[PDB]
Image 1 (cartoon, helix red, strand yellow):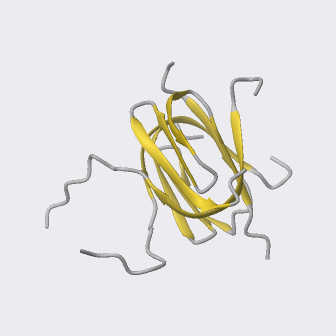
Image 2 (cartoon, one colour):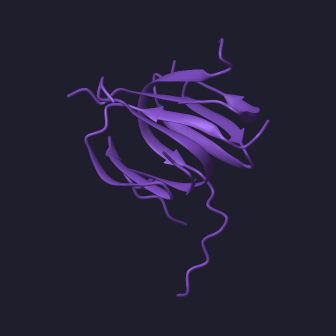
Image 3 (cartoon, chains in turn cyan, brown):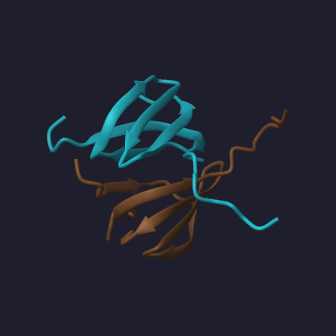
Length: 66
Length: 66
């Protein structure tokens, strides 16, 4: 079926990197990493077109008991 | 600037849990979890506004351990 999706975000703190195979943008204070394939201004907003095959974001906050 | 940001996503298979302090949307690959505060329609699209302080997504797919 259609697994393609669009992801948009703004208020980015800085552009750590921008690649069609991986995009890294730091927002607020954490860093968001986008992984997928075929990831190809105004309002100061940015949009992205491609299928997300994975997402990784450090959750520096989890401690858990065991 | 600021910490508030706009985030929208489409092509979601089904909503698992929609809460203002937590959102779990079952989309391609698996389920995307979003954590923060104040995280909250035609076209079948979903829009969420708020400060994202943490993001957790399962990057399994293939085995990778050391």
